[PDB]
Amino acid sequence: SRKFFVGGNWKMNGRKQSLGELIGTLNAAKVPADTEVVCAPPTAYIDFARQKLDPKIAVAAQNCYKVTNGAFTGEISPGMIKDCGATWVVLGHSERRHVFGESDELIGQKVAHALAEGLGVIACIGEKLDEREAGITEKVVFEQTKVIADNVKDWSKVVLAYEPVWAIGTGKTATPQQAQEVHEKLRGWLKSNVSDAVAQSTRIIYGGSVTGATCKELASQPDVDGFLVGGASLKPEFVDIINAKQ
Amino acid sequence: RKFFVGGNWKMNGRKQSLGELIGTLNAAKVPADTEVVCAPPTAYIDFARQKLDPKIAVAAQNCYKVTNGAFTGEISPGMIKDCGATWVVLGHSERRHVFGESDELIGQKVAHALAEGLGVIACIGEKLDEREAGITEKVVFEQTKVIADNVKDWSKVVLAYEPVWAIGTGKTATPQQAQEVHEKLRGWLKSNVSDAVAQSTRIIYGGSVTGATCKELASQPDVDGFLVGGASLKPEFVDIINAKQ
Image (cartoon, rainbow over the protein chains, first blue to last red):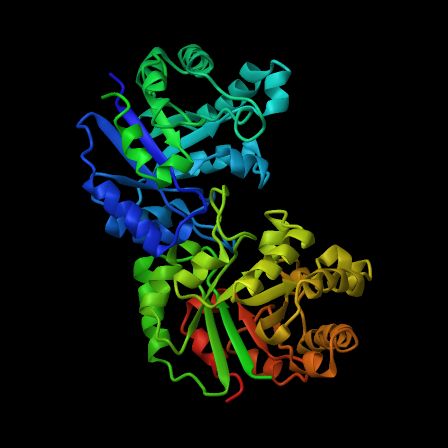
């Protein structure tokens, strides 16, 4: 009875006008009473988006730092995110890990701090192509999930997101079968290393390529509890994805 | 060279405290000969620009090097301008040292911000080990070199010297020591752009600036203003604004 969860990661896109249009479209959409929807704007627009979005849709920050205030030019804290009316933060996103070199240790510390501060956390994991081709998928994602888990003391406030980085912009593609395969392994990890209750209740969402044409087959997979949508989150197609269980 | 006072709020404040600070700043009579800029946390650029009197400019504390893209957690110069900010701080010691931002990356950010019509406060400075090893000039020159390459119009760029060697290290910079580096920096420039540019480029001091020290620092020949840290969050900022009065 895990509630379907659909997150929209806008990444580094949009301005007040275009994001205004996006928000208008989302406000007009009728969201199924069974679905939790979250939008993650660029950091400059967290406040803007929260003011314009219907309260039915939650706002997430795309990143944060690991202390409440300090000499960290260019960063923001969970306290600031909460203060802007946002209730989630995305942490450990593949782009943070692999373009900006954020370490597993750092990600763990951010998870610990965000949760301590009462923010919800969408914690991202996933293996690169070199890791997939080496058949080291499980090893990588388990190592990443372990660090997240060691820094969580209330799982009701976290959602795990699997990003098949190996498929995104490298050459390969992910099928609903291999998505389900990883999700099933992840939930088994939670059962084995955390608890039965945490395994049953924790939403594990898919963060690979998701289109209106592929979201139904993906959402019907037993251990896929929703999506963290990239590019399609900027377009009307996002609404189709919200209705993947319909 | 118009006196330039920037306040770097760093990762501090919330709507309530920042609203009160803005109230105090709005009430301040800003000197006609002083250009004042505040750099709020990224989440608050929009908020700050809305609340601040137009007499004070707003800066982002960082940006990335393309207009839009798959860069979760970043913002572009286009977004910064869209929020009404007119400057970005680039190459801050905290970005360089805590977040491992390379000189190359900083240079590309400078080029992009300038191309997109933003002004840039470009930060440089040596650490204690480099100072002690006698490599102040090598370090600061390499950093400035990578910046200059990405500037083909100095009109919209301010250089900020941060004595990183004096931050929590047990050493402090004297006004004389500040003046000494500012002179060397300008000398690196004057030879390398024009007499008009090294003569026109503002080099601001990013070390410890307070009400007690700002007057003496502002009086140094090659010191064109400040990039203020902690005092920027306090009424003390107004005394620093008043440094040349």
